[PDB]
Image (cartoon, helix red, strand yellow):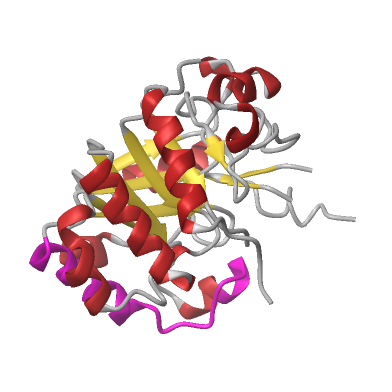
Amino acid sequence: GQVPVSVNYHFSRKTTSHVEKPENAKRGLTLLKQAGMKKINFAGGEPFLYPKFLGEMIDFCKETLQLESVSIVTNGSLVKEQFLQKHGRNIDILAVSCDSFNEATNIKIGRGSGDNVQKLYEIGSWCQKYDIKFKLNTVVNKFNHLEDMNDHLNALQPFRWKCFQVLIVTTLRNAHSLTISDDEFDRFCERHSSQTCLVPEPNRLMAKSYLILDEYMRFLDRNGQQPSKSILEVGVQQALQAVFWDEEAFVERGGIYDW
């Protein structure tokens, strides 16, 4: 460390929850830039629950820090067109997490009830109006691994469709009651082979260099836990050693269900 090119800033957690003051976050992200950060991704709580902060920090990252890439991950429920217009010049990628187009499937995963589907189409279209790359994030699990989505994906034309094989971390067993074999996962990917945006990520080979910065601007370790002290306190490289930072061990948590 040097930090990876990309850092995932989970600036609030899933009353309500702690969020950094804008001056402090502005300072933390500056530290990250000086340490090698070029791309930022706002996750994981639900960023559009806090649009004034999201908007301030998007502008700051693109205008002041001149970052190559500014991404957001969202369930899409609270995205309104006024935000994308006010800030779209500064947002490169908006990823919407969508696991199913069936209301029943969604309820069973722990998300519903729908109908989410028209809102997704609204967002996809606002993305082209405001020059935002439109990405879809899907976790393939016991409940959606037989679903056919080609029609909806042909309509939505994301520039990237990332499909993660579910992985659960540990009275539960309603985990192994949710895993899928690699064959089931592959049969989902083939079922959508006609789909050029499709980027599969199986458990056998997860993306590396995946670093999470939490709502106190602390890093998490290779398991999503044992946070360092905030970079605001000990700075970037000392906080990296505090969490045993190693590019190859920090796999992507996007497909993971952290329980």
Whether residue 112 is in magenta: the answer is: yes
- Would you place residue 196 above or below residue 203 in this image? below
Q: Identify the magenta region.
A: 107-130
Q: Nearer the viewer, residue 149 or 68?
A: 68
Residue 142 image offset from top left, x and y in percent: 59, 55
Quarter holding residue 152: bottom left
Instruction: Name the spot of residue 60 as percent of width and height, x first.
Output: 30, 50
Left or right: 131 in relation to 233: left
Q: Which one is in front, 50 or 97?
A: 50
Q: Nearer the viewer, residue 35 or 205?
A: 35
Instruction: Tell whether 173 sits left or right of 137.
Output: right
Question: In percent of the image, x 37 and y 41: which residue is there?
Answer: 40
Residue 131 in percent (x, y) is at: 11, 58
Q: Is residue 102 visible?
A: yes
Would you say residue 24 sits in the magenta stretch? no
Name the residue rendered at 52%, 32% in the picture: 211
| Left or right side of 150 for 48 | right
Q: Main secondary structure of the magenta part?
A: helix
166 or 147: nearer the eye? Answer: 166
Residue 83 quadrant: bottom left
> Is 242 situated above or below 26?
above
**Residue 36 in the image: above or below residue 191:** above
Residue at 58%, 37% in the rendered image: 232
Is 225 above or below relative to 23?
Answer: above
